[PDB]
Amino acid sequence: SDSAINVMKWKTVSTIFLVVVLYLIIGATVFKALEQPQEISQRTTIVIQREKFLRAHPCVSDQELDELIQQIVAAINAGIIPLGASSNQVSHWDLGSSFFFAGTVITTIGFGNISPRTEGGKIFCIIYALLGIPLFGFLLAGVGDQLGTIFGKGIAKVEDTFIKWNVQTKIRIISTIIFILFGCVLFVALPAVIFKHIEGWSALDAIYFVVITLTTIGFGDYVAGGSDIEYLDFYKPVVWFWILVGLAYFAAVLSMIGDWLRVIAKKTKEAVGEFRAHAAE
Amino acid sequence: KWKTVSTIFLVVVLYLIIGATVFKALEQPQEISQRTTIVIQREKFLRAHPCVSDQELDELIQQIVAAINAGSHWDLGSSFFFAGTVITTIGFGNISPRTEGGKIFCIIYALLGIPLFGFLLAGVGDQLGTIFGKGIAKVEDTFIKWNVSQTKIRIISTIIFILFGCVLFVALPAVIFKHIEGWSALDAIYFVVITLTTIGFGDYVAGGSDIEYLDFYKPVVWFWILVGLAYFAAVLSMIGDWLRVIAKKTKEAVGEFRAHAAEWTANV
Ligand SMILES: CCCCCCCCCCCCCCCC
Ligand SMILES: CCCCCCCCCCCC
Ligand SMILES: CCCCCCCCCCCC
Ligand SMILES: CCCCCCCCCC
Ligand SMILES: CCCCCCCC
Ligand SMILES: CCCCCCCC
Ligand SMILES: CCCCCCCC
Ligand SMILES: [K+]
Ligand SMILES: [K+]
Ligand SMILES: [K+]
Ligand SMILES: [K+]
Ligand SMILES: [K+]
Ligand SMILES: [K+]
């Protein structure tokens, strides 16, 4: 009873582990099947642009070119505009950017477009995160509570007008759809349409960014406050504000998918029992 | 009835404002020195090589700027590790999908893989939670019958979680990273924090800088991540409870003061 269920626990964990391993193997085989074709073509067309510049300029230091490229690669890790023209650059750590950077830290999005290179900044970031991450979780919980109860008001009016004859257990389906329906409008679609017309992104690049942002994965390959274009500055505030509330939306969405995985686990759990039982033994 | 959210919001805003002012105070000094020493290293290359001209350098820079979009990537092992960055929401970003299908798959792979990982991390966190429960049962006998009372023992037993934990999940993997990737002292601890906090800037990655590492190394990293995430998950939530107490202690301390201030105020 005390450590007898602990055996029933460890058997549950190991089985999850392998489902995750398989899922990482499946995802692996899919991604390289999707990216390796465009990898090689970019890998092979960059050696041609090497030989095109090695040979056309014999007087350049033929092998010290990679020495230069590595220094530009080292410059890439900083915020740079290394050009003949445009010798006055912009601050990547300005009064507004460091504010947005702190938002990447406590939310654990961490786009990485701007990362600290100072040993003091590194240590502060460590202390700023370890105390700021729990701080934000309480704000996100409070906002998630507000949205949870804001939606509770808006669904109360919707769960009475649909009360015809022969309607509670099958109304919980239609009311969770309007959460997704309205939800992916205000927190995915509408901010994606805005990003498309402000950052110049494509259709998918906007939705891809919203997902990567609000899933707090944050690759940083797309960031709303990365480039220099115009940035009204009525724009950088509403972004992290959107993030604050949008995170609360996916927090439910991801957890709803989680419960959808609970059921499908059980339903395949019993269906494997059905199948191994019957079918002419 | 009462909100209590708005008050937290402003504490977070001020914390983001203070953190902002600190970060640029820490980085903008080294921002200038690196931006001024790149302009010198650019004239150093125009002057030392009359071979290359003003117009031909900027053509090269834009090609490397075009290479920023790309840079063996996405091999049989790398895409496996990349999927680990997605479901754990670490997302180092050193390797990101450039294909329309890869982006769409990644969206679907995340929306369904993030909850999937949540249950595995919960199961491992359960094991560590009960593995540690065995380790403290022996610690809560041998010197607890002796002088100190047990409400004051809840202090010493939570220290051994932090003390022995930041050894196995921060220090020891950082010492290994220091001697395998050649990182410095802080760069190892900085990576462990950024990794296990799920922030994952990607400025340091155990799978990148690909010259020197073996096939006995890339498995153990994600394995360490799986268990180390469960460790910070508690650590961050414990710090959360520290704040939840300190809030309530300053909560009532302001009441104590606003009591006497207004209590004398009425008496005038
Ligand atoms: C233009 C981008 C659209 C991307 C939308 C992705 C929607 C996901 C649909 C996946 C359908 C599979 C359902 C399997 C149920 C477990
Ligand atoms: C010898 C260099 C060791 C660097 C370790 C600094 C870590 C600071 C963490 C602060 C936590 C309170
Ligand atoms: C009146 C309620 C204010 C809540 C106080 C929380 C502030 C915690 C600061 C911790 C700094 C290390
Ligand atoms: C009462 C409903 C408030 C909805 C706010 C919508 C926020 C959109 C953020 C972009
Ligand atoms: C969620 C689908 C997982 C497929 C593996 C099934 C093993 C019983
Ligand atoms: C970072 C410390 C903030 C303290 C705020 C106290 C508000 C009563
Ligand atoms: C390992 C460092 C913990 C220090 C805690 C300080 C609490 C006042
Ligand atoms: K992240
Ligand atoms: K990142
Ligand atoms: K990230
Ligand atoms: K990068
Ligand atoms: K995260
Ligand atoms: K997290």
Image (cartoon, coloured by chain):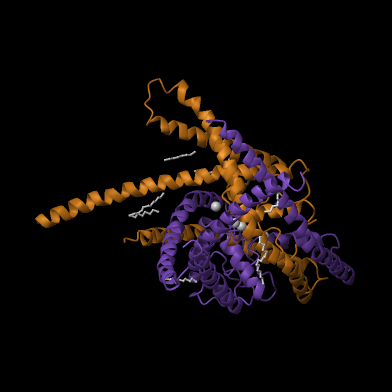
Chain colours: A purple, B orange
Q: How far across and how far down the image is residue B139, in percent?
A: 49, 26
Residue lying at 51% horizontally and 74% vertically, measured from the top left: A235
Asked if one can make out residue B23 in the rendered structure from this viewpoint, the answer is yes
Q: Give the left or right position of residue A52, taking residue A20 as reference.
A: right
Between A144 and A77, the one lying in front of the other is A144
Q: Give the left or right position of residue A83, taking residue B26 as reference.
A: right
Figure check: A152 above or below A235: above
Between B36 and B193, the one lying in front of the other is B193
Residue lying at 65% horizontally and 75% vertically, measured from the top left: A203
Q: How far across and how far down the image is residue A163, in percent?
A: 44, 70
Residue lying at 56% horizontally and 54% vertically, measured from the top left: A259
Q: Give the left or right position of residue A243, taking residue A206 as reference.
A: left
Q: How far across and how far down the image is residue A1, in percent?
A: 53, 31
Give the quadrant of residue A273.
Answer: top right
Asked if one can make out residue B90 in the rendered structure from this viewpoint, the answer is no
Figure check: A13 above or below B101: above
Q: Give the left or right position of residue B186, taking residue B152 as reference.
A: right
**The N terminus of chain B, quarter of image:** bottom left
